[PDB]
Image (cartoon, rainbow over all chains, first blue to last red; front, side):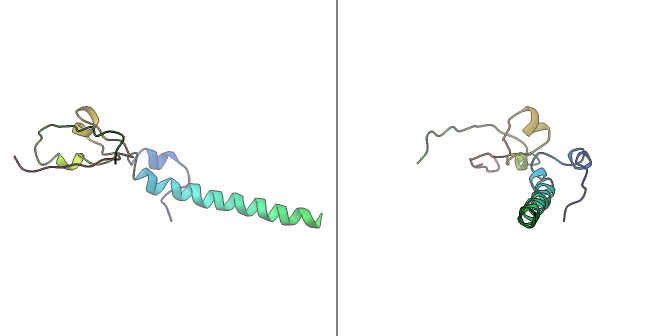
Length: 48
Length: 48
């Protein structure tokens, strides 16, 4: 839902607090992606 | 109840009273009197 996936283009145009509206999204969808690789590897490991 | 009350006081033109808000950027909030992005506090103001 946010504007860019390389970080500085945001840091260069917004403050310290609409930062907490526009960096957290990327952090969340990233955390979710890590949570999928780790659970999918944790299920995958039980096949192995 | 609060661990302390600290009260900060000054007089400013109305075009800048908005800068008396959390994490605000700009001249008066940047170099005159300053609030963090977490300011666990209030602003009380009137035309004087």
